[PDB]
Image (tube, rainbow over all chains, first blue to last red; front, side):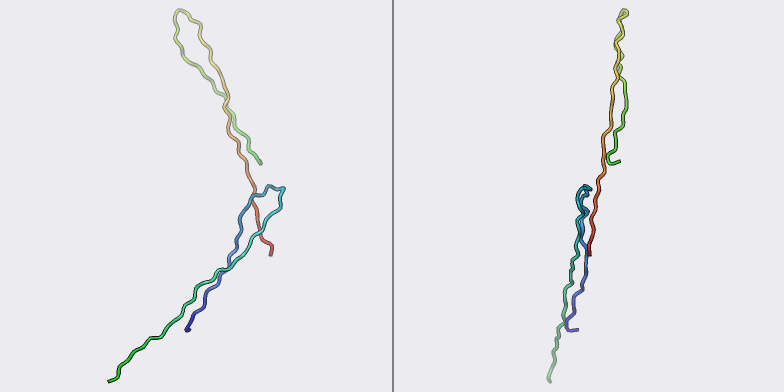
Amino acid sequence: PQVMDAKWALQGNCVFLEHIEGEEIKFGTINAENGPVARIQTYATGFEY
Amino acid sequence: PQVMDAKWALQGNCVFLEHIEGEEIKFGTINAENGPVARIQTYATGFEY
């Protein structure tokens, strides 16, 4: 194409906190990160004789 | 266990002293040597989707 699209990815984030056992558990998250874009140009030249 | 108990040992101490004209022999000693203590924790988290 004249321009190309990014690439998408998801990841999950969670940290193993301590469990004193008299305290309720804590939860994690997910987030997305995307790739970069590219585009292509045209060039040309010629003669006239 | 949640906490692990130490380890014990018993040792003795004696010093070869000099002996001149039936000097009464000196007498030794004993003592105790203990181990350290260790314990184990809990870690936990999760997701709710």
